Image: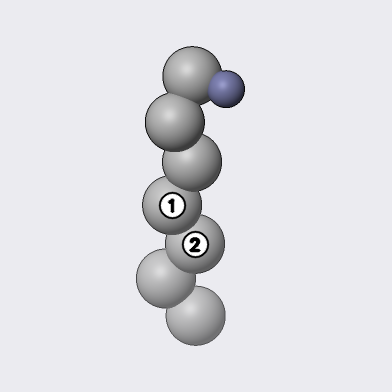
């Protein structure tokens, strides 16, 4: 799957 990190 795809991953996104929003710090
Ligand atoms: Zn993946």
Q: Distance between the Cα atoms at labels 2 and 1?
A: 4 Å
Q: Position of residue 3 (x, y in %)?
A: 48, 41
The image quadrant in which ligand 1 is located: top right
Query: In the rendered view, would you say 7 is above or below 1?
Result: below
Above or below residue 7? Residue 2 is: above
Disc 2 packing (10 Å; few <14; some 14–19; many ≥20): few
- Residue placed most toward the observer, 6 or 2: 2
Q: Quadrant of residue 6 in the image?
A: bottom left
* Residue at 44% over, 31% down: 2
Give me the disc on residue 5.
2
Indicate if the residue with disc 2 has its beta carbon within 8 Å of ligand 1: no
Could you tell me if the residues under marks 2 and 1 are in contact, i.e. CB atoms within 8 Å? yes
Q: Secondary structure at mark 2?
A: loop
Residue at 49% in and 80% down:
7
Residue at image mark 1: 4
Can you give x and y, in whole percent of width and height, for residue 5 in the image?
49, 62
């Amino acid at each position: 799957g795809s991953n996104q990190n929003n710090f």
